[PDB]
Length: 174
Length: 174
Ligand SMILES: [Cl-]
Ligand SMILES: [Cl-]
Ligand SMILES: [Cl-]
Ligand SMILES: [Cl-]
Ligand SMILES: [Cl-]
Image (cartoon, rainbow over all chains, first blue to last red):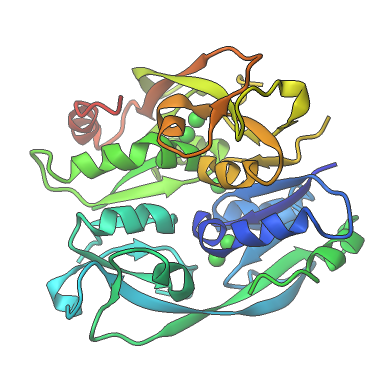
């Protein structure tokens, strides 16, 4: 049946859509579900055998789960203009997981949504640098560091699809 | 504090991002959360006062909830080529709610994800016609009807923010 991969809207938009595209020419024949849901729902679904694979930047409680570190990607603080300091902007919140972090004018889990809004909310937000570089009108905020996130695959250790999980994770995301 | 609006990834991508943009120049001062989550989580969150407003194409069980019909939008079956019949294509599944509907090669809740994938999966899928028209390389499948969905606002009838819900719903989405 369908192999389900779950992740936040921003991971699908910024990196997993390309990776999923490569799985259709991999040496096997599968149908896929690209599931977009909140972290607590996806983690519960792994335990209930309702989700096959979770991709995330933070490992959850690991009892009865397995994890594999896939890589690491850079994160920078972007705005729509050059030469701006953070105190001249509205800090918008793109969700990056519980451990990553005035009320923000906008909070969301979609990088594309926060990118569209940033140009009309005098905004800045933390975005994946590789994805942000191919957008127009993004400039790093001057008083800011380059940060990063790890990327993990999480699955049920006793999953009935451990064989297919092992082969899918041979295709690199980063 | 933040006013939370919840909807599927596809409603945010196809129509609610523009609507949210108009709320920042409305005659009031609010900060917003554009929440993307699965239907069962958003409905539970309304009941638990964790979500202020749900936008959806299908009314859930309505005990202790209120609803307002906002409008109706057309849905057509699109593929990447002119003059194709559905039996020449791979039918991909974009989620449209429990009542809307071979294993599909792809199933997702993001219209942008299914649009990117459609060009490499010989695919067709049901997309909002207004949004699809501004994309390049989409053509309606020849043997297919134009369908539609209603658009509803759902909220907790006894919400402590009924006043702000009433004013937000005065800004038209469609
Ligand atoms: Cl995730
Ligand atoms: Cl969810
Ligand atoms: Cl994540
Ligand atoms: Cl929805
Ligand atoms: Cl919906």
